Image (cartoon, grey):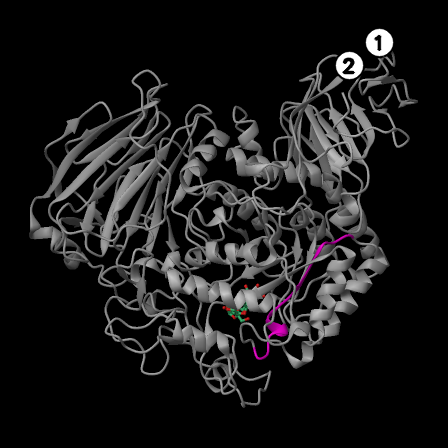
Amino acid sequence: DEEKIDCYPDENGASAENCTARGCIWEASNSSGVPFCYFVNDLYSVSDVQYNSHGATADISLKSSVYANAFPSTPVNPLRLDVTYHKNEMLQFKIYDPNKNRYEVPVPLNIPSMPSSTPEGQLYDVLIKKNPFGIEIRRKSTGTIIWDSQLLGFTFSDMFIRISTRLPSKYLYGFGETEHRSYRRDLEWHTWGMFSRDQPPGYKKNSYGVHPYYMGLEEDGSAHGVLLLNSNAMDVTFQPLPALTYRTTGGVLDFYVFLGPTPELVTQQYTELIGRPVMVPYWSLGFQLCRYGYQNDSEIASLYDEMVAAQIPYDVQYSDIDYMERQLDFTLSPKFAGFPALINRMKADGMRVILILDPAISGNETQPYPAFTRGVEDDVFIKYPNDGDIVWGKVWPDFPDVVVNGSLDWDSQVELYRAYVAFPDFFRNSTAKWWKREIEELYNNPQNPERSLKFDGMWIDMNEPSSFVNGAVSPGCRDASLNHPPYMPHLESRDRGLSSKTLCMESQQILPDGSLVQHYNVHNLYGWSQTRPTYEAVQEVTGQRGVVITRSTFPSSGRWAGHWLGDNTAAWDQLKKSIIGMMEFSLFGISYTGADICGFFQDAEYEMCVRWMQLGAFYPFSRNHNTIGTRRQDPVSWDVAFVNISRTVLQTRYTLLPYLYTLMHKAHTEGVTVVRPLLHEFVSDQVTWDIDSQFLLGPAFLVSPVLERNARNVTAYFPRARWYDYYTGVDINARGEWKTLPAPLDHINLHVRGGYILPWQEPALNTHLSRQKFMGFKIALDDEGTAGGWLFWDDGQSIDTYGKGLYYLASFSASQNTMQSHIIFNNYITGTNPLKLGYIEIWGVGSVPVTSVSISVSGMVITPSFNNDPTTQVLSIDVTDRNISLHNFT
Ligand SMILES: C[C@H]1O[C@H](O[C@H]2[C@H](O)[C@@H](O)[C@@H](O[C@H]3[C@H](O)[C@@H](O)[C@@H](O)O[C@@H]3CO)O[C@@H]2CO)[C@H](O)[C@@H](O)[C@@H]1N[C@H]1C=C(CO)[C@@H](O)[C@H](O)[C@H]1O
């Protein structure tokens, strides 16, 4: 019943007779999922298999065209397969057309100069099996088979490619941006669309980015990863005979396989290929506020003052498109003048500001508008292929004189008001200068130095590329590269073709080299194409490292940006989904992510929002954002009870920051994960393979959120190790056990894994005041493991600090009743530049209050006063009275 490989996934025309017309068998079923049409025999035949020291290659040919000609596109013949043993832990196999040169995804990866696999170290082996044509990847370690495409269905036609594989288990994690219902994916007959579209998160709905990458767990605790470097419109299909099926619409099958043995190891190797996450500015680790519909310039300032009055910490203040004049890029609303004043005032207190940008530029404007005009001069806009005019979409920008009724039909609004806009082609060496310029002159206004906005980071959005008309504008598109492209993957609005909510597929773009591409192949690449330049733009203009949040992603996208999970709604299910989203994104190679706290779409409710601020207080990207007409949902818009709660939890986060920052350093340097599923640190425990309603920050910080309304308690899992409550210092004392811990409406549960030391620092009102206060230690000893730890210090904003010069790297270790410090490299904390070392806490020291050594060394040796409770292992040791800094301490 499984093993049935759906022969008719087509949008239209599945029928007994139409089914027979391919080499296929029609047989109804009463079981949900099973394909009425299925494969009984193959249509390609592998021929000249050959192996060598460094790879393998066979040839694939039709047999015969009688049936291959019967489905989607004109099949390609013959094909060719090249497997390559890059490293011992990594593979690639590609199936392509050796004759014609097919579209291949233009995103740089790093690969050993030549194949560096060694017969003794190589951890996997491959076999090109012959009947029917198959590919079998195996972990040499223990025979588990990683990939096995010796199933039927393999097709390969210009605009339709199918390949399948048995999964080595019933546990698979993560696919290209959408709203999964659990971390581990179902397998019980589910298809998923993958294609950049402006879709609020939804079940089986294709969303902002595309990520054809998964991690599979094996029989034993072993793990592997698989990437399909294809950017065409595709959908994947999970069958209960553990096995999935790709159906792309026309690249080549370029697969890369990774078999680090562990989840982290896998990710380290995936990111090693596509690139590791961007290092973020220390200030971005703080809390963030925004909304769609900040009315007046001053309604923001009103908010920023209300927030410092409540003493709720936060470093980043935004403004949505409201600050633009009629949603035009690079313009300042009348209603928002002396907004430039607000920026400068806030940053002066130590805050920072992030501004949104859309990609589409309006060209129906009457006044002068350099952005658009110089756009046309430098020729940076996306046109049709036969020289044809700009491909005109519509988005946010309003027409010039039109008077706007905020309440009109959303459709009516799009014809009467919204201007025609052009989409820049961000591949082009030209579009880079143009874009980078506009950004320059936003920062330093050539004409009105008083109207300069001094932003610190950019939020590129609406870049799928999203558009509020299907394709182009007035007459439409004209093409079959667009609608019904032989196979229309299982996307949202399938009936609308690929055109739906974006550019015409025939739209011409130009790659950096200079060759011509149509939007059809690079659509999923669009937002990605825009990411690096924007990143660079911010860097050049601000002279600092800065940060970029983008909506549309693609593998490697996270190399220059972070990501927020998009248009959630203020509903309870959406909290848990954010935990997933984050987790999945760590896999996808993007460390800096989160959801819109309290919920974008719709009005926030009180209790849900107390719970969400507590959860979100631990997103790496912690931002409270919100759609237009809704009521405001920020912390100082509820009541005294709320405010006070918000304060406490935010404080906690501003304490973890030195830890959260080093994680970010380690993910950037090592490939490791930041938001990390328990199962990454405790694989041998199968209970964790399924838990997705709680998560880790790094290895030692266990977050256990309350995700249900009335609930004021929670049941959370606690793997086999010591879990110290972060607040009290006491070990919970569960071990591979489920405990029900009390969870009052003011409290969120956090625990520190025994065997780790966490560097902390006193909570300020923003990271500027914070970095000045006292540095702490939390040594979470475990009878289960003594203690290990890391700290990395930086000016927190300079470009490539680690990579060239000024940083501080210290590993910490506690063997016997004593913690010792080893500075690996120091170059920013010097005698003159001191790091105040405040307190030193130690949890789990013993019920016997007897020390053999109570005094700390700096070179000299003091025996400062301490507090100790025998009941609770805590051993506190204040030191706010010494000249102790991280650079002279031992
Ligand atoms: C702010 C948001 O506006 C537009 O969102 C539209 C969505 O495209 C559609 O999904 C559509 O229906 C959704 C409903 O609005 C919503 O109530 C939900 O419950 O389900 C519906 C899905 O069927 O209507 C939406 C109109 O509001 C736009 O497409 C979307 O991309 C916009 N979000 C971005 C815009 C802003 C402002 O620049 C940013 O603040 C957001 O973060 C962006 O994500």
Mark 2 Cα-neighbour bin, 10 Å: few <14, some 14–19, many ≥20: some
Does dot 2 land on a helix, a strand or a loop? loop
> Residue 499: horizontal and vertical position, in percent?
34, 69
Tag shown at residue 368: none
Of residues 671 and 414, the one nearer the viewer is 671
Of residues 148 and 320, the one nearer the viewer is 320
Q: Is 226 colored magenta in this rendering?
A: no
Q: Identify which residue is drawn at 61% across, 57% down.
A: 542
Residue position for label 1: 852
Q: Identify which residue is drawn at 49% across, 48% down.
A: 558
> Residue 154: horizontal and vertical position, in percent?
21, 44
Q: Is 314 colored magenta in this rendering?
A: yes
Quadrant, the C terminus? top right
What amino acid type is highlighted by mark number 1?
A: Ser
Residue position for label 2: 817
Judge whether 689 appears above or below 52 on screen.
below
Q: Which residues are magenta?
A: 313-326
What amino acid type is highlighted by mark number 2?
A: Asn
Judge whether 191 appears above or below 601 on screen.
above
